[PDB]
Amino acid sequence: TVPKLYRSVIEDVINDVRDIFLDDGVDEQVLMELKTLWENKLMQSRAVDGFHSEETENVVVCQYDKIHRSKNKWKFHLKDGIMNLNGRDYIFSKAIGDAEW
DNA sequence: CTATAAAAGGGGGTGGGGGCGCGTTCGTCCTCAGTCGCGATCGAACACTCGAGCCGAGCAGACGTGCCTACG
Image 1: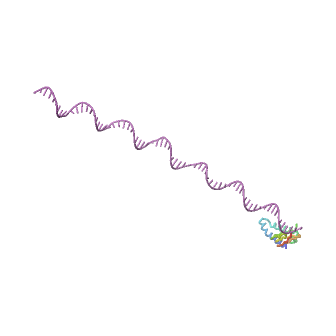
Image 2: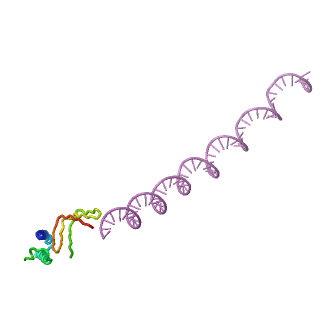
Image 3: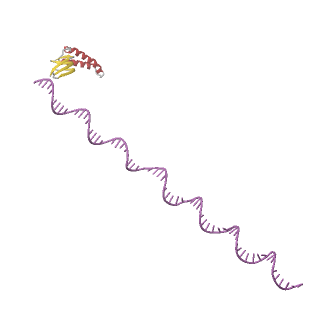
């Protein structure tokens, strides 16, 4: 669920930045060095298992719809987020958060 | 202990008042036509002169009538 999105968006940004670099004048081997060392760093971080491998706190970043406060109680309407928990990573697109302050 | 409510303090915004600067209007300046005083000449009248002409007086005389004497 995570490497599928990572492969799709890394090939998306590669096939978009091809014209960006060749309109800024550099060799295609420089583009290849970008993608190659970028997957080297995904090897180095050692959190998700994928392709180039076979060849600090818990932060959740996201977006919100509404944060509601009924006096003590908080209600979070979070959406489109990438969680990093227990070392590993997960994705979500919706989250309801009940919070006692 | 944590949450909610109420109270107090601080900050911001709006309104009012005061001060300063722009604006207005009449008292004070600025010509300019109509008229006064004086020389300046001009026309009308007035005083003086001078001669032309007429009139009266005056005087010498003539042209007559009457009135009176030496000669035939």
